[PDB]
Image: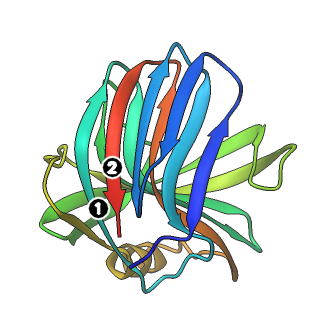
Amino acid sequence: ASTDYWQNWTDGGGIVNAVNGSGGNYSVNWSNTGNFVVGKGWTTGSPFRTINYNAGVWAPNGNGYLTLFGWTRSPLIEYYVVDSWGTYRPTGTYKGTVKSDGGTYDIYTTTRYNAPSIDGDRTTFTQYWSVRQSKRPTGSNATITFTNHVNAWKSHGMNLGSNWAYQVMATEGYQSSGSSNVTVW
């Protein structure tokens, strides 16, 4: 499907060279950054969407995530479906696991305090995570059947908001360097 949203946010630290390529393709070169999130997807997320992607390049030199990323409002929730990472595997409060698209993911919840949110400014919000137990190989056509995650989360009392914001396959980094090239559809 044609992506219609381009996500390019940085807290201003270091170098983040994000390129908005043709179609659903994008690339990022980053160096000694603070926190940043880049990716392509849809302006309005959906719990029934099936995300396809191919990371032709996934080379983080430190903390970085290759992950589905999105937000909902009412309540304000940031969610993730992490397929690969760099030197640090994200974790939090363990809830359970979910099997989807050939992999097994751990379900976690965390909370951010006085952190930047989608609406700008700072606030406290909850984060929902699905983190693969082992890194998913890249360079191949991968699929993320989001409904499986949404349903698994629901079974653990992890309900998303009623107002859906953007939903994208992104590259997120934190005080690191690296490169990535991803195509989303």
Q: Position of residue 172 (x, y in %)?
A: 48, 39
Circle 1 SS class: strand
Query: Helix or strand or loop: what does disc 2 sit on?
Result: strand
Q: CA distance from mark 2 to mark 1?
A: 7 Å
What is the three-letter code of the residue carrying label 2? Val
Task: Identify which residue is drawn at 43% across, 86% down.
Answer: 48
Q: Hey, which residue is sitting farthest right in the picture?
A: 121
Q: Which residue does the image show at 34% across and 36% down from the upper left? A: 180
Residue assigned mark 2: 182
Determine whether label 2 and label 1 are within 8 Å by CB: yes
Instruction: Report whether residue 78 is seen.
Output: yes
Question: Which of the 4 image quadrants contains residue 9?
Answer: top right
Query: Is 56 on the left-hand or right-hand side of 179?
Result: left
Q: Quadrant of residue 149?
A: bottom left
Which residue is identified by label 1?
53
Q: Quadrant of the N terminus?
A: bottom left
Instruction: Choose between 104 and 178: the one closer to the eye.
Output: 178
- When the figure is inspected, residue 33 is found, relative to residue 113, above or below; the finding is above
Residue positioned 43% across, 27% down in the render: 29
Between 45 and 97, the residue placed more toward the observer is 45
In the image, residue 59 lies at what x, y percent?
Answer: 27, 28
Task: Locate residue 133 relative to residue 131 in the image: left or right.
Answer: left
